[PDB]
Length: 49
Length: 131
Length: 62
Length: 45
Image (cartoon, rainbow over all chains, first blue to last red; front, top):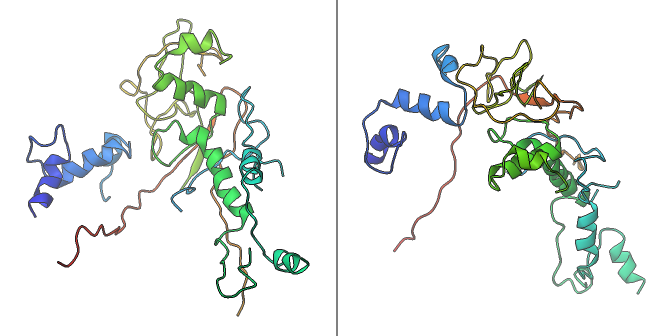
């Protein structure tokens, strides 16, 4: 459960592990921005995803 | 199922200009695959010609006893997986994501794969090739 | 839902600095647009472009 | 009963173009998500 807590902030990264507290939604817009390399205009318009 | 998924070139006799690739299927079990199946010594298998062919005379079908089952896939189809894999060598080796891409010729795939980690940039691969 | 579109590989002009890619390909046509992996397609690039050396098939820029 | 299907493979083969342009198969829909594998870690002791 602390691992699920660290999913969002640790999934950022920028180093394992010296971080963070970022909401989970923004963690999946950066995790989604990363390798499904759709940048910000698609995740802005739209979500729902 | 973790091999193929996407997306071949497809197999045309010219892959890369000019990289003579033996891995082409001549037509179905390509040429280098033919070398490492001919040079390997297997006394097996029998699939409606080798049982009778041994009856004309390994004994997975004569002691019975033990019995060898066939390997789930015909050789033309494992050849189909790895041949679409050779198709996806060029475009998938680009990347920019696995796998949602592409169709790029094999020569340019090795000038970007060669540009990458043998980090010689474009002036060397331009002047010259042959490589 | 796969849709086959067309590259380059980049761009050039009368002067020759290039583009392509940050990080995904192309540079489509209609006109030169860039939402790549996965969906499509963006605007004029402006932050979607490192500027490497020119290559063959001159001026666009393969 | 009703044997012998041969259901392979078949990848959506993008075709290779000739000139300075080269085709590419980008998609349109996300469609996330799967459950995935167990990794066993231990025995019963």
